[PDB]
Image: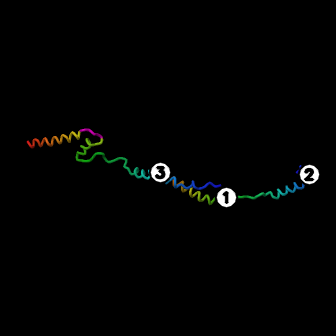
Amino acid sequence: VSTLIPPKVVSSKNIGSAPNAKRIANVVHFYKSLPQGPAPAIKANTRLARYKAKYFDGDNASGKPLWHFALGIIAFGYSMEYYFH
Amino acid sequence: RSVLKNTSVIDKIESYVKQYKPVKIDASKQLQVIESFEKHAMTNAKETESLVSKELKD
């Protein structure tokens, strides 16, 4: 006798699958993400975004700003030594 | 019939067979039920097809 009609309705393998939850997530997350960004280091732009670019990028952990800032404090109280002299 | 020597009863059953030579006439009944079944089946089949095709491109 005639083969039954349950297989001709699908709406329980289309909404009844687990990656649907991931699908609706990653259509929003990925589709709505700019493939590229603006600029990594730019804070303090006044030729001191350049200071950030040379020293406070994630492209270096080089000791130069530390040295520079340290030397600043040496310059601060030392000048004041000759101001207090 | 040529075996039987009492033949006039083989002529009888010959005539009974040829009388009742229609032993039952035509049956086509799948022409009302098959079409009804086909409408619902087609509808559901196309619905599923369109839904999943849409989802594939999605």
The residue where tag 3 is placed is A18
Residue A33 position within the rendered picture, expressed as x and y whole percent measured from the top left: 38, 50
The secondary element bearing badge 2 is classed as loop
Identify the subunit bearing mark 2.
B
Q: Give whichever of A21, A31 is nearer the camera.
A: A21
Residue A32 position within the rendered picture, expressed as x and y whole percent measured from the top left: 39, 51
Looking at the picture, do discs 3 and 1 lie on one chain?
no
| Image depth: mark 3 or mark 2 in front | 3
The secondary element bearing badge 3 is classed as loop
The structure residue drawn at horizontal position 45% and vertical position 52%, both measured from the top left corner, is A21
Q: Is residue A66 left or right of residue A36?
A: left
The structure residue drawn at horizontal position 71% and vertical position 58%, both measured from the top left corner, is B27
The residue where tag 1 is placed is B30
Magenta segment, which residues? A59-63
Q: Is disc 3 surrounded by few (<14), some (14 to 19) or many (20+) residues within 10 Å?
A: few
The structure residue drawn at horizontal position 91% and vertical position 53%, both measured from the top left corner, is B6
The residue where tag 2 is placed is B5
Q: Amino acid at mark 2?
A: Lys
Q: Is residue A10 left or right of residue B15?
A: left
| Quarter containing the C terminus of chain A | top left
- The vertical placement of A67 against A10, above or below, is above
| Image depth: mark 2 or mark 1 in front | 2
What is the magenta segment's predominant secondary structure? Answer: loop
Q: Is residue B3 left or right of residue B53?
A: right
Quick one: label 2 or label 1, which is nearer the N terminus?
Answer: 2
Q: Are marks 2 and 1 in contact (CB under 8 Å)?
A: no
